[PDB]
Amino acid sequence: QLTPFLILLRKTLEQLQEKDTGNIFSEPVPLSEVPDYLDHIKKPMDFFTMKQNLEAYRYLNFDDFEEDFNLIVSNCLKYNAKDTIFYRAAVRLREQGGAVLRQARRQAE
Ligand SMILES: COc1ccccc1C(=O)Nc1cc2c(cc1N1CCCCC1)n(C)c(=O)n2C
């Protein structure tokens, strides 16, 4: 049901954000500091934006939620060179966030 699902997602988002130990993915990539970001990235995403989306009832299924998480990672791997803190952090988040989502999905099913 909807209310239990939304409770699950809120907890899941909290746990995903907990894996961002560099605090690298918790606000939008700042265009004032990374001015060419939108030359390469179609749809920016970050955990604050996901929280706004969650609280506005925009994630009513697990796939839509997981897709936005996957964008946080994919965008970062795409934009940044391999030998950067950003790329390395995204690879780690993919692994550790992946684990959180697998557990959450087992709960939702
Ligand atoms: C607020 O961010 C900055 C402030 C001053 C100088 C530089 C930055 C900055 O480069 N931030 C930044 C760049 C990112 C980035 C994240 C950030 N910040 C780092 C500081 C906290 C907010 C997010 N991700 C995920 C990327 O792929 N890129 C290129």
Image (cartoon, rainbow, N blue to C red):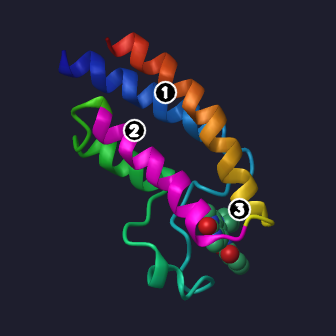
Q: Residue 109, how many percent across, how many down?
A: 31, 11
Q: Which quadrant does ligand 1 occupy? A: bottom right
Q: CA distance from mark 3 to mark 2?
A: 20 Å
Q: Are marks 3 and 2 in contact (CB under 8 Å)?
A: no
- Vertically, is 97 above or below 103? below
Residues 25 and 96: in front is 96
| Residue 90 drawn in magenta | no
Which quadrant is home to the N terminus?
top left
Q: Which residue is mark 3?
A: 86
Query: Mark 2 vs ligand 1: CB under 8 Å?
Result: no
Residue type for callout 3 = Phe
User: Residue 92, located in which quarter of the rendered image?
Assistant: top right
Indicate the secondary structure of the residue bearing disc 3. Answer: helix
- Vertically, is 35 above or below 52? below
Q: Earlier in the sequence, mark 3 or mark 2?
A: 2
Q: Earlier in the sequence, mark 1 or mark 3?
A: 3
Indicate the secondary structure of the residue bearing disc 1. Answer: helix
Question: What stretch of residues is rendered in magenta?
Answer: 63-81
Q: Are marks 1 and 2 in contact (CB under 8 Å)?
A: yes
| Residue 74 drawn in magenta | yes
Q: Which residue is mark 1?
A: 101
Is 81 left or right of 76, judged from the image as shown?
Answer: right
Residue type for callout 1 = Leu
Is 97 left or right of 87, judged from the image as shown?
Answer: left
Q: Which residue is mark 2?
A: 66
Q: Earlier in the sequence, mark 1 or mark 2?
A: 2
Indicate the secondary structure of the residue bearing disc 2. Answer: helix
